[PDB]
Image (cartoon, rainbow, N blue to C red; front, top):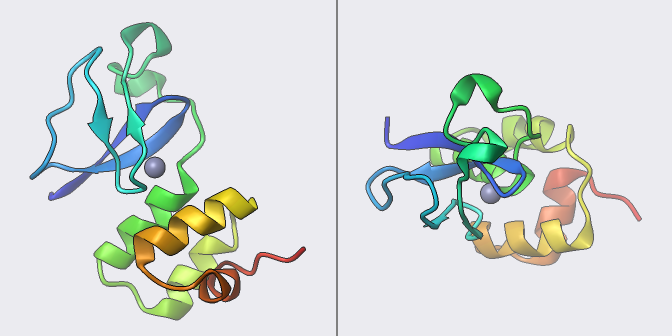
Amino acid sequence: QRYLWQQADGKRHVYDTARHRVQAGRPFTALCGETVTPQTERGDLTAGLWFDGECPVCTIALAKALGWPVREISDLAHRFDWSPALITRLAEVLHCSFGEVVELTGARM
Ligand SMILES: [Zn+2]
C-alpha cells in the first residue's frame, strides 16, 4: 500500500509512504499538502484512538490517486461540507480550476 491514513492536527490525513515515515513529534506533508505533526497525547500514534474526522481534501485525493471514475469521486465528495478554503486547496491538489471543484463536490453557496 503506497498510501496510508494517519491522524494528525485534528484530522485523518493520507500520506505517501514513498515520501514520508510517520514518527511522533515529526512533521509530514499529507496528500492535501498540509504539513502536520502527529502527537501521542492526541492519540495520533495509537490507531485504535483515531476519532478525528477525515481530511476531505486527502480523501478525495486518495480516491483520484486510486483511479476512481469521476462520478464515484463526486458521490464521495458530496458527503463533505466544502468551505471555500477546502475547495481552493482541492483545486490546487487536483490541478484543476475552482469552478471544476465546485462541480465535482456539489458545493453550493
Ligand atoms: Zn489532508
